Image 1 (cartoon, helix red, strand yellow):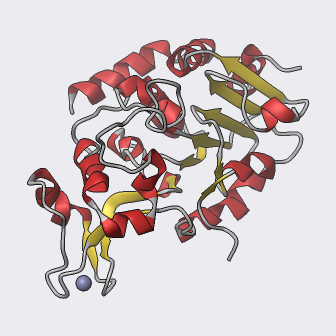
Image 2 (cartoon, rainbow over the protein chains, first blue to last red):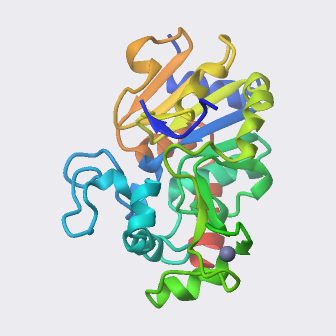
Image 3 (tube, rainbow over the protein chains, first blue to last red):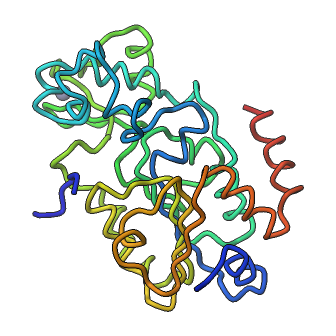
Length: 8
Length: 273
Ligand SMILES: [Zn+2]
């Protein structure tokens, strides 16, 4: 749900 | 405040025996693969006529579906075969052979952990793999070799059944991580030492794993620079060995008494590849 691959 | 030598002693005295590891692209630059965020050399700085409208597109779906050739160009370059593991991978392998490796978590898609003989069961390939592929239309799975010839030949791999583009099981931005990643729920509490190697920790949810070990657990960083929570909020059992990662690893190997065994293992390895 909110556990996708992203840059912080 | 703990030292590298302290960490070596904990392992030598068998006080630490369940090591979890986290790695990033910094462990593969010494094999010739440039990283993401190093000024000048890093892929997010330098790629004019990679044919990418900006560098991050490489792993973005909208762009992949508009034009998949840049991605398969990186695939051609990175196909397990044309780069070798280096001392950092052999050290991990040796951690496995000596019975110390709980689990290795990698953000890398170069395959060099498997190439070096670390077994799949000890490996979490958090950002996916080229071992297998999936048709983007009909979801039929294919072994990763079925697309090796297409990439060598500079073809876009397609599905024999629906003609859709077939894509290695690499994680793109916005997608969740393979379910194997969920092993962290068990692994991190069970660990009695954490090693962090060659990463800037700027990608989630992979980065957040640094926090999932217990507070009595030492966190050892070997990296060109301080990063993540060792940068912004250190725990008391944190250790940073700053410099070139192969040098950091070579010091540790020396403090552990494994220098001949290491260079032995390379032999039977980089030789027999
Ligand atoms: Zn298909």
